[PDB]
Image (cartoon, rainbow over all chains, first blue to last red; front, side):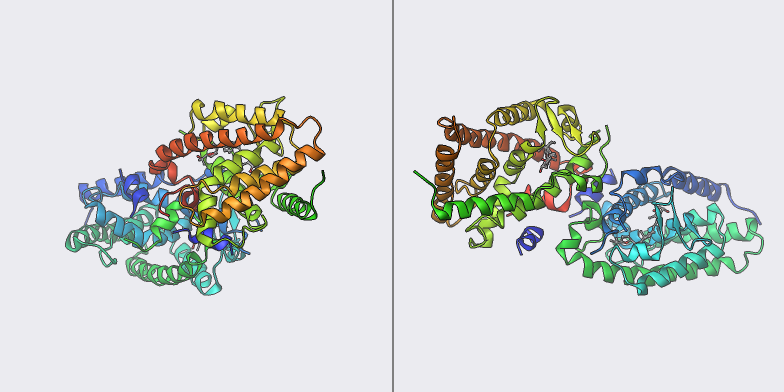
Length: 10
Length: 10
Length: 239
Length: 239
Ligand SMILES: C=C1/C(=C\C=C2/CCC[C@]3(C)[C@@H]([C@H](C)[C@@H]4CC[C@@H](C(C)(C)O)O4)CC[C@@H]23)C[C@@H](O)C[C@@H]1O
Ligand SMILES: C=C1/C(=C\C=C2/CCC[C@]3(C)[C@@H]([C@H](C)[C@@H]4CC[C@@H](C(C)(C)O)O4)CC[C@@H]23)C[C@@H](O)C[C@@H]1O
């Protein structure tokens, strides 16, 4: 997963 | 899924 | 012509259930993330919805016959109807003078521009407020109000429901109690029942506009991280 | 013996990053779900954590060399180290007089019994507060504080990290700047560096106690529905 994580990291 | 849903329904 | 003892037993069950799941003080609204006036209002309205879904679930668990469906069917009806029962029960705080929902104090009064700040466009919200005024003008009794919810929720024309015939049975048995209550106990209500079914049809049209806009919103993680676990689950898709 | 221009360039980057990701006013705490004093404090502390994770992510994106790792490695380091950097950065609000974390006003002062009301048992929280007093007694400079975070975070002995050798390189290169800063710029710090590495070891022991208790908590949906999407993702398991 890590949809939110990956996006916060740009 | 529906972990929360199923549990709220007891 | 008069109502059977079991249709009152039903009416009694449905209003006591609504009174258990509806706080007219709106005193739990202080425990949400506070409103802020992008998408400033999304946190506070996301908790508002998540809270309301918990209330809608408690209400459905008390409709006669609902407990006895299979848990899968209960989930399918809730997932498909959740936003509709919310739009329905929300009429109780809606008010025609302010043309907004005035709960508790004035920090919890949501005009149309508050909901835009939670990421929704006027083509959802104009039919929404019109729904709420049209329904506010029908001036339902408490009994017709809880019935229309119980009926909307127990509708079998939902995606994903299995024991279709049993739900259609229970829905109709509640429609009979409604149509019968209006004839006996509501003067001037010879056009009401059809006006209620028409509100159910508007609820569907709203349901789809909202489901579309939420889709666009839930697929942007800067915004879906503002939602709650429960909201994500009930309005999500992996069933 | 004196520090190279690039180790200052590093020190400068790390403190400006910390100042960007740390609000000494704690003025965003009003936007959390309010504290309430089961598990009354879980909502407010769940937003507190979720907010802090957003801050830790912004800080890591500014450590030199971190941006250039692969996104998978960045995720693995964050998921494994998140609760540790939180325990570290949290020392800045911790205070020895109240033996609690005093942020903003007194509604945002968390003694040990507040965190118990968010579902945690004293065998996590006694080593936690002792960690925080032992580290409060080391009286770190801002420079050693940001370094110890950057170092804890860039540790390669994490579950799931791939380019192990590159992270170990970057971690050591930051340890050299630390050990060098203490020798030059910290009087009385000839035992400090080892005391800092020992705090990293305590962070690991805390990490595991917390990871165990959170597991027990996240597997009960009455409680995990109080968490946020971000928390669930970072402390979750499906990597
Ligand atoms: C939910 C209730 C109340 C108000 C409901 C409102 C007024 C504000 C705007 C709301 C919450 C609508 C909007 C479209 C919600 C807010 C969040 C958004 C999401 C779920 C993010 O798409 O839908 C649905 C019902 C609308 C107040 C009170 O009657 C309790 C009732 O359950
Ligand atoms: C997080 C920060 C601050 C305080 C942190 C604290 C004090 C209260 C208790 C906290 C939040 C701990 C507990 C164990 C948290 C709260 C929620 C719980 C979950 C994640 C539900 O397991 O862990 C971790 C750091 C502890 C305040 C300020 O320094 C900002 C800093 O990022």
